[PDB]
Each structure stands twice: as structure tokens, then as C-alpha cells.
Image: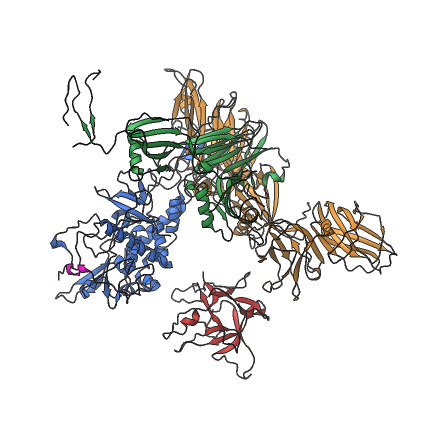
Chain colours: A green, B orange, C red, D blue
Amino acid sequence: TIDLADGNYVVSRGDGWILSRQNQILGGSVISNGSTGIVGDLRVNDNAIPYYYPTPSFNEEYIKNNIQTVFANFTEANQIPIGFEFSKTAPSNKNLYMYLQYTYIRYEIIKVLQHEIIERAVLYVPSLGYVKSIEFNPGEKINKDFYFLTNDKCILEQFLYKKILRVLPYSNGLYVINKGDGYIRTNDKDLIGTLLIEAGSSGSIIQPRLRNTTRPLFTTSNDAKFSQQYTEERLKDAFNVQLFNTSTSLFKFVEEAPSNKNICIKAYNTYEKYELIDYQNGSIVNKAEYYLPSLGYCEVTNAPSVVKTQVAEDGFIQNGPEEEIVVGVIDPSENIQEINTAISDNYTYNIVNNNPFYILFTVNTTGIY
Amino acid sequence: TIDLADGNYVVSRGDGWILSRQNQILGGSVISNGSTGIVGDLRVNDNAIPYYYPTPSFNEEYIKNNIQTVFANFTEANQIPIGFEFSKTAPSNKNLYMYLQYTYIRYEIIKVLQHEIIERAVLYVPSLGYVKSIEFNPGEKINKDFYFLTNDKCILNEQFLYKKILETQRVLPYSNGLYVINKGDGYIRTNDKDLIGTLLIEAGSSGSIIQPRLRNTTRPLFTTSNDAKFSQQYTEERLKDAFNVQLFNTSTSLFKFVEEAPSNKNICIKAYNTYEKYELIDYQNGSIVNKAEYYLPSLGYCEVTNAPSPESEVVKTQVAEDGFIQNGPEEEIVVGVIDPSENIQEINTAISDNYTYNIPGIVNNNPFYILFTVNTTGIYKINAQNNLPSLKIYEAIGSGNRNFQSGNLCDDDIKAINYITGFDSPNAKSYLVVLLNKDKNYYIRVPQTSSNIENQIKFKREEGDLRNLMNSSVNIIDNLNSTGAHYYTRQSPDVHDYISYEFTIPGNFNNKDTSNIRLYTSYNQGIGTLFRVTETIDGYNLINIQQNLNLLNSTKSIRLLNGAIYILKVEVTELNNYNIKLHIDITN
Amino acid sequence: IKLKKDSPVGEILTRSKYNQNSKYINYRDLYIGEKFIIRRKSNSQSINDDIVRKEDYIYLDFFNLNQEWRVYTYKYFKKEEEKLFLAPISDSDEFYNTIQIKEYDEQPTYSCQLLFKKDEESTDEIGLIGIHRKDYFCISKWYLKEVKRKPYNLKLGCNWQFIPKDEGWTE
Amino acid sequence: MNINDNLSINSPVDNKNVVVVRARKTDTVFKAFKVAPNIWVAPERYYGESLSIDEEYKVDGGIYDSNFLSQDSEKDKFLQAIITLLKRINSTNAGEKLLSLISTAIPFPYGYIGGGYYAPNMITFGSAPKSNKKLNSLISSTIPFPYAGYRETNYLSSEDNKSFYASNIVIFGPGANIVENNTVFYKKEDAENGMGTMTEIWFQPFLTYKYDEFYIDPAIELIKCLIKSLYFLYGIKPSDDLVIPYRLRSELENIEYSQLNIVDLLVSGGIDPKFINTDPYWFTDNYFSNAKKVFEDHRNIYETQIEGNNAIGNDIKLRLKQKFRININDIWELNLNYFSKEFSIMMPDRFNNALKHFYRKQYYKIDYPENYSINGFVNGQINVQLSLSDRNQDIINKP
């Protein structure tokens, strides 16, 4: 039962989905009085295998392609190991048992006929983990619902559906503009993960850079002049960016929930926006945008006490501060001559053939020339 | 000088044995002005080799074999790299120097003659590390005892565990079938066979024992009372069916234990490997006819202890028997599984208001399962040809959450089943009245049949008053054609579960001759309700007659009509016997 | 072929071999699999004669446990390679039971062919029993075209032989 | 396996499927197009051989021309031809299996920088902030320090020597001699010691020749080159001195023999291998025993050490598994006869390695989307209409 037009729909129901009958298949930890137990994992290879539950008319390839095109791409994102961990401190005279699960992302491909769903396939992407902890006494009876889960449920509840079908006083030249470092993509396309930290516990997400491969994003309005190599060369000329698709700087986010209520921490992958503009007579005749993989973004939220929301259009949201650094660069198409002697008091340079060009020089003494 | 009988003995002297002259071989660090310094190591392979000191009678193979037989298997345990680290913040402005050394387990094998030790061999197994720190000033002389150790010594409890060398109930209301029971987490072995290691933290310091999962190899344990059918592969398959356990001898899940000692006394942390216990039981006729135990490697267990007073003599204590100790919480989760020896049929079309299923010839009079789904949530009456045989109904746990195709059946291949109702007596006459949800896969178990006549299983969507007997198995009584007393024994359901008996009173219908009917039970206590039953074209119209009865040794009778067809519904509120026994005393 | 425990379709299994004590002698066991029997269709010939002749309609049964089961095929199917139906002796209006045994190789051979026909008086022809690739024991309508080629193919999947228990073959 | 058919010589260099790498450690670079996992095509001629050889060094029966594969149109035609041949091979089950084995048979990686395939070191990062009662200095995350540090040897290095792309096979163009398919290793020591090495193939897909009453399918020549490359990938390469007597030179007045390397005999198929691969073997060398022992050693090294390591990637750990799934006898008993039978391709069957002495070859040009196709030669191997190449006049004849 749904309120939508007839046809096929790609739906994301968020992450933090724990499956049924497989809660403590990974095992747990018993912590005696005083000590701290840290239970973690590093999603890289085999636990990073999606689970397909397809139907007739929705094969694996169909659902996979649709979910990559609309929502976040997992085939390339699963090659990069992402680590998560929980820390729990046991009481001074008590024993604490904590066990780890896997939280996935529930993706669906529904077929709406009339105002009811007649078909539904599911695709589970391994997102992160979840530690459930209890404080127990020897011989104490524990509720059976603490360990076992009869049916799947979300521990974080969304339904995102998509129907399948100012004056610039700059001289004429080439400019590179660093426009900020907070940029994430819409529709949670850059979601590293989300952890639900219980009260009195600590959670952590680390990008350990075990595989130093990053994916920048390039857009352009003229591939003839502003190409990948051209924009990379201009960035290296302006800000001396030496690494583009490989970063060895690794980042971690740690959050300690208070003893009153739980908390949720969402880690995203960010970008740095580098515009490259060709300014000519007060008008940007060519603009190429580059997005350099940055060191992530952290969000803290609390679970609310649903509404079928249409997916958002493609774009970027900046969560960093307002930045605008403008650096002019030398046009590579114009020749550059040099004067190998400092200008002292009086110089005449004799002039390439009717072509604009640069002259590089220096003065022997500070002064007005 | 010992107080044991003559022979050979395997002795463990505990953890925390620091060797002589080996101090300051890994190095040390200098900090000052309240600066925190961390030092750690990794016991992987090369710095994790044993030291053998044999004797002509006790060769290396002999001591190694005996030690690994009685105590922890150090050969297979040193293959897994285990990390540790210490942290010690500096005090106010005085330089502090710390240095790291190894600790060992000392394994002596001795030859006791008379009551004097005449022979001994030593085995040193590298366990963990130990950090010793001092506060110094530039140009200050330090005692030689701090730096250089002349003789081997123990920095932990003075253990002495010796073992002589020898020259060689409860009522379960479960239905018949295979069950997998998670019996809890935190199972360690006796005699420290699972001890990752002990770590001693000085006052004002912190220590951590870490499993970094640099190697995924883990060692599960398996015991079985019948290897012919309950093998390790079979138990692994059943565990995968029940709890979806994917990895058995491989694990990638880091666990780390960190302890900060108070700044008045030292502390010790013992890290163990734990196990999750799974019992695969074959349960028939109210008794465990087969049992296998599978211990899956868990994520360890940390124990915090205080250093004992040095003014205490050693006590030669014998080792404990081979067994397991549970340190985690009390847990017992029972999940029934489908017997793999029985074929499973399928009904692709969802069951409508009416459906009849003919038993195929490929079964050839064998117990089997049929998998079916129902188009609309409702109460269904499921029976067979003249209510023979008595058939059971299950419910796949977690079915319908993932896949969906309206009007069809999606085989989710879920082998974990939850028993709903039914009987295990093939000669009994009964039909199930159950409640089926719109998007759940259900199993019907047809038992062993001893007849060549083809059968038809009928599912009838009941919308009348039969909703009263929700999730029950109406048991037909037909051999009631005389006076006296009758007893009927059935598989008693669990607490808050329903059973039913449809019976008829001997004699013709004359609206008179109200025979005295006394319905009671023998062991189990249950709330009983009686109904009168009126058969129409659309079904049954339950008519309430008595409610809130007490069947356990009931001594009350009812002046009840003759020739009529009544239904007695029993909700067991106290389970005392595996088999329920309904007694009906009829008198004129 | 071996009868499957659950599915009513014979599964294809690799034959055993001899690796007991001698590397100088190698062979494969032939007394493995289901014991097949052949029965008459109409009992119209002479009782004294009991040999199987070419182009003969018969029932091909096999002994399962302590019973005899016949092999049938569906009336209608889409794919050329259709699996068989292994069931106890029964009468149905939706399965074909009569098998015509024939010989197609002009040159001398010990291999025979099994064809499925709608009726003894019906020109309708269903297919030929064979094995097609996971190997699967099925019937194919593609064998009909390939069996009439002038150069006969002796390595086809339709060539079947029957091995009785002989006093000259041990193990 | 799925051949990437959406590539062309005009595609931009995206550093993922179209790259510009350096040829060995020389001063020359070349473009490369990845058409399958660890399978690349270089549509230009080979770089090692000079295209203008002295006349005194040209081999008999070889078309020498230093202008072939020089324009972009010819390079694109070569690339499309290689794509078509690979797709034709992939169509059949045996060809798909061979291509999958080629893709998954990476050379055995080396150990860590200090030696060994066991677990690596450990490093703790990210100490938690100090709390009000606890220092929390040891509350950090432990990670393997040299993660996936096994130093693979099968890679192409970019022109800047900063980007590296994994690759097993590079299909170049023909070298100095136009009609000469060749298979050359990347490192002899790593090719003869059971480790493994990169392989480069010089292929000429545009010229074929007629034998008896049929034309030679270039797909079978490519298959032979791939099978020979499998020898280098697994490191089972016998010494160049392991030869067998192939033919007796009856045309000469002295008793001389022409000999063939055992690799060529084992790969070329035909009838000659049937006279050596006999049960029992009459011809045996220490090479087979050494190769089996080294392969078993490497398989044990993987199974006991490189298998349980949880700090290396499944991109290598799981290809090494599939590479070591097969046995050496599978490679040795794999020749052109099996692919000829499974493809129904007629090929020379007697002394196919000495066809230069027996008769003179006439070369026919192949237009690929005109004559060849996904199913092979149009109108079969016999009734295909192929025009005689104009280069037949340039065949150098040295008796």
C-alpha cells in the first residue's frame, strides 16, 4: 500500500539495518570490573559483499545499475577499507557483555500498480557495525529479545524514492578559485557511514588509508581547452597540488555519548572545490570545476521519537566555512622570456612575433619604477 | 623437596616469568615534564619461540607433547600475533625512564622419587611483555638491581599446577526434530588452555592487550555423541541454517582490553579467548536422542585481578578436569531447523480462499515438508483426507522481510522454522486451525504414512466463529460410544498454547438425557473452555457454554446434552509433564 | 545416471575407477547406477520370442528401492532439452510413456536409440533421449535432425547401451 | 570475462582504461588500452626491435616494412581487430576459460620489504581525548601498518613513474618482421624460477595465408600466443637448451637435424606432440620435476602463509587462489589441438613449425568488419573471399 503513480521506483530506506537471526555470529566480549573493552572491525573485502534478493523482472544487474545511478555507488567504495569501533567501560564491581553486529543499507526496487506495491527486490550494502551491551550478574536471566532478532529493523527511518524513466574586477586571464572545503554530494552519495552509540559508550569511524586511492570529480564546459590534464596542470601551477587521485592523510572521528541518551554519528567524504575560470572582458567564457577528495565531514544527531520523500537533484552542499581564494595563473599558451640581470636604474629590453608574452625580471633595489 | 608420589609430573608455574640477563634488550624510552609515553610490541613469530631446557629422560618432543596435552597449546597459539602496549605519564618535573622486557610461562616437568625432585626440565613460552620504570636525575647513580637481573623470577602470582603423567530433570515441550540452541557466550577452557596472556600494570599506568586480526585463522571446537550423522560438517551446515553463521575458522573482528591502574597499587589483566556454544540436538519423543556441541571462537574475555601479597607460600594444587567455564551472561535461544534428509515441496501459487494439494508420488510414503504462502492474512483450517494423518505446521523465521511478489511465492530458502501447532502421532485424527499472515512462508510437515491411498491436503479460509480456536490443533474423538471413563494422551503444548478436542456424546438427540461429563487432566494445569458447535454450509458457529475452568484434577461435572458435537479448548498454564492426558468421565 | 533423493530427475554422476592395488590395470565400473528393465507395450508378439527387435514400442522402467518406476515426458515444452519424469507405474493424460527403441547406425554397432512418440499409430514425434550439458539427462528434439546425416556421428549423446550382469566381468 | 569493446584510438587518456606508460625503462612511451582485467592492447608496433633492420639480417620469408601501423587509422583498425579476435575467442566456453585463466594468473608477488608472507606489523592511531577521570591514552585503533605490502611485479608504470597499473598481457603489434607472431617475457629470471612474469605479444591480425584448401584463422594464432604466455605467467619456462629433434634436414648432404624447443612443441599441437607425450614417457628431463616441485612450493607458500593473512587484499589473495587451483599438468597438456577441436578450426597438422621449408606462403589481407566477425571467417574457413595482399611482392627470399 503506497501513494505513488504506477511504474518502477528505486527506494533507499537509509542505513543502520540489522538483519534477523544473525546478531552474535561475530561473537562478543565479556569485560570484568574496571577494564575497558574496545570491539571494532574494518570493512574491506569479504564482509563488504552486498546481498541481493531479486524478483522476476528485477535481476541483479538491473537493481545494481539503478542503485548506482541514483544513490551511492558501492562497488568502487567497497574496495577502500573503512574502520569502525566501539569502546565500553565496565562498572567498578560488575561484568559487562557487549556483542557486535553489521548494519546495512536497505535498497529496494518496487513496482507500483494502482496504489499498491506488487513487487519488491532488496539489496543490502554492508555499511558499518553496532555494539549492543548489557551489564549482568552471574546467574542472572537476560531477556531473549536482547540477543535474538526475529525480523529486520532499522535502528536509526527514511523512504527516498526515485521513479525509473556581482562584479569581478579581474584582469583578462586564467584564475583558480578555491571556493571552500566542505562539499558533500546530495542523496547521501558520499556517506561513509553512520553509527548509533548507546549511552555511556564511545564510537569511532576511521579512514585508515590502507589503500591510498581517492576519486576526484571533474566537470567542464569546454573539453577542448579545459580537460582533466589541463585543469590538473593549472591546479599544480596555482596551489602546487601534487597528489590528486591518491591521499595518505587519514582522518578519524570519535564521539562519546552521554549517560542519559544515545547518539548517532554520521561520517561523510568531503571535497575541495577548485574552479578554473578564463576571464575575458568581464565575462567567464570558460569554467571548469574540480573536486579534490578531502578528509571527510562529521555530523552528530539524535534519533527522533515516516514521509515518502522524493529524492533530491544532483548537486553539492558545502558544510565548511565560506572560502574564496583567487589565484591568477600564467597562460601556458603564451611564451615567457627572461632577463638574466637585475634592473638597477635604467634598462631597455628589445623584443616571438606580434604575440602576447611574458617577461620575467627582478630589480636590484626596492623602489618605484 | 616435594610432597607428591613417585612418578613424572607436568607442572605449570604461571605467567609473568622474566628471564635473566634479558633486561633492556628491546630498549627503553625517556620522558619528562608530565609527557605521556607509550611502548608496545607484537608477539608474532621469531620473538615468539619457546625456550627448551631438556633432560636425558625428558627430550624436547616429550616435554612439548605433555605440555600441549595438559596445558595450553603454545604451538598453535603463537601462530596468531597478539599485541600489547603500556602507557605511563611522567610525574611533575623529574625525568622518567621506562624499559620493556618479555614475560614467559614456565613449564617444568619433574621426576619425583621418594618425595624429592631428582630430575627437572624447563619450557619457557613467551606470553606478553612487562615495563619497568624509574625516576632519575642527570648524573644520579641507579641501583644495578633495577637494570640487570641475575636469576629468573616471577613478577606475578606464585602458581604451581601439577598433573601426574600416566603411561598409556527439565521438561522440554519442543516438537520432534532438530534444534540449534545458543547456550551463551564467554566459554573458556579450564587450566588456562585459552589464556591469551597476563599483563601487570604498575600504579599510575595503563596497559592494553589487543588482537589486531593480522591473521584471520581461528580454532573452533567440536564434540559429538554420534559422528555417523552429527559430523562437524553437518553441525556447521545446521548452524548456518539456524543462525546464518557464515565464517567458522576465519574471523576479522578486533578486540582490545585496556585497563588504567589506580595510582596507589598495581593491577593485573588476564585476557582469554572465549567461545560461543551451540548445541545441535535431535529431539524425539520428549528426549534428546542426539546431541552435538560446537564452540565458535568469540571475541575474548578480560579479567581484572589484584597482585597477591608477597607474604604467602606456594600451594601445589592439581589441575582441573577438561571442561568449559561460562563467563558471559546466561542465554539460551532455541531455533528449530528443517531436517535435510526430508525433501521440500513448493506451492508457487498463493493460497486463496480454497485450495487442495495432492500428495505427489515422488514422496512414496515418506515424511516431508511443503512450502506455501497465503494471499491474505486470515485464519485457515488445514486438514487432510478424513483428518489423516496428523500434520504439523511451522513458520520460517524472518520470511517476507526481503522479497515480495504479490500473488506468488518467493522461496526465501530459510531453514530456520518456528513451531506453531501440530501432533507427532501419525494415527491421530486432527486438523489445524491456524492464523497465517499475508507475507510469511509456512511449512507443513506431512509425517510418515503407511498407506497406498493418495491424500489431499485442504486449506479452507475460515471467516466464521472458528477464529476462537486460533493457533490450535482440533483433535477429533470418535471412539466415544459408551459410558465410563476415557483417557487421551497427546503432546502437551507449551505454556500459553492451545489444544482442542472435538468430541460427540453417545446417544440419540432428544433434547433430554443430559449425561454427566467430567473433563479433567492428570499432570498439566490448563484453563478449559467448552463450546457447542453448529455445522452449517459456511462452517462452524461456536456457542460459549463454560469458561475459566481448571482441568488439573477437576472433580466437577456438567449435565450436558447427548448426541451433540462439542469442542473443548485447553490453554496450558502450567507445564509439568511432556505429555498431556485428558480424562473424560461420562455417566448416564 | 542415479536417481535423485529429492528431485524426480536422474542426476549425472562420474563413474568410479580401479585404484585398488595395481597401476598396470585400469578400468571403470559398469555395474553402477540404477538397474533398468524393459517391458512390452501391447503384448501382441509371440510369447515364446522374448528378444528386443529394432523399431519396437516398449516401456523403459528402472528398479528403485523395492519398486519399478517408469520414465515419462511432458506433452508440451518450450526448450528443446526437456528433463524426464521418473515416477511409479501410473496412467496420466499429461505424460507420454511409450518409448520406441530404434537403430540408426548403418554400420555395425552396439548402440541403440530411444525415441518418444505420441502413440503407436500417431505420426507425432517428441524427441530422442540423451544427455546434454552441468550434465543433464534429458530428451532433445535437436537430435532428430542430426541423426539423419549421411556421415553418422557415433559420439553423439543419444547412443545408449545396456550392460547386464555377466560372468566375464567382475567388479 | 567481458571484453571492453567501447574503446578507440581517439578515446581520451583517463588513467583507468586508456593510459600512456613507459616501455620497460627506456626513453619511449606508448599508449595502452585495457580490454579486460589485466589484459591490455598497444596498437603500435613493438619498441624493442628497430623497424629498419639491415638487409643482411632480414630473415627468410618475412615481409619487412617500416611504415606499417604508423597512422592513427591503421592503429584504430588494429585495435578493433584485436577486440574482435578477443571477442571471438571469448564466445566459446574453452576460449572464455583460457581468457579467465590468463586474467587471473598474476605473477606471484614478492614478500614484504624484510621478507616473508606472514602477518605484517601493527600501528595504533587516534588516541581518544582525555576524560575527567581517565587518561584514555590507550583508547585508539589498531591497524596493520604495511597493508597490502607484497610488491607485485606485474605492472605498467606511467610516464611520470608515479602511477602503476596492474597488467598480465600486453598485445603489441608486429616487430621488424610484419608476419611474425612472437611471445616475449618481461624478466627471464622471474620467468624460469616459478615466480611469474609479464608477457608481451607481437601479433599481426591483418595478413593470413592459405594451407591446403583453407585459410588460417588468426584467432588460433592468438590462442597459441596466449597459451605460450601462460608458460611465462606461471614461471614454468624451461632453459633455452631444452630442445628436441624436430626434423631431419634431408635436403642437405650432411647429417643435420633441425630442433624445436619443448615449449613450441607443447603449444603448437598437431601430430608431433603425439610422438613425445606418450604413456609411458620415453623423453623425460629434470625440467618437469623441478617445475612441479617449485609449483608445489609456491602453492604451499600461498596456502599456509598468504591465505590466512587478513592484511592483504582479495584482489591478489583471491586471484592467487584461482591461479593455484589448477595443476602444472593442466598447462603442459594444453595445446592447439584442443582449441582446434572445440572451435572446429582446421590448422596445419604435420611439422607446422617448419612450414617455411615445405612451401612458399601467399598472404591474404583481412578486413575485419568485412571478412572476420564474432563467429569467425564469413562463409566458413574455405569459402571466404579474401584478396591477395599487395605485400606478397616484398617477401624476401633467402634460399
Coordinates of residue B430 in the picture (x, y in percent): 71, 57
Q: From the viewer's perspective, is D105 left or right of A19?
A: left
**Magenta stretch contains residue B32:** no
Coordinates of residue B366 in the picture (x, y in percent): 62, 61
| Residue B199 can be seen in this image | no
Relative depth, front residue between C155 and C167: C155
Coordinates of residue D313 in the picture (x, y in percent): 39, 42
Q: From the viewer's perspective, is B26 left or right of D381?
A: right
| Residue A110 can be seen in this image | yes
| Vertical position of residue A31 compared to residue B279: above or below | above
| Vertical position of residue C43 compared to residue B184: above or below | below
Q: Which residues are magenta?
A: D374-399
Residue plotted at (16% across, 63% down): D256
Q: From the viewer's perspective, is D300 left or right of B107?
A: left
Q: Which SS type dominates the magenta stretch? A: loop
| Vertical position of residue A24 compared to residue B133: above or below | below
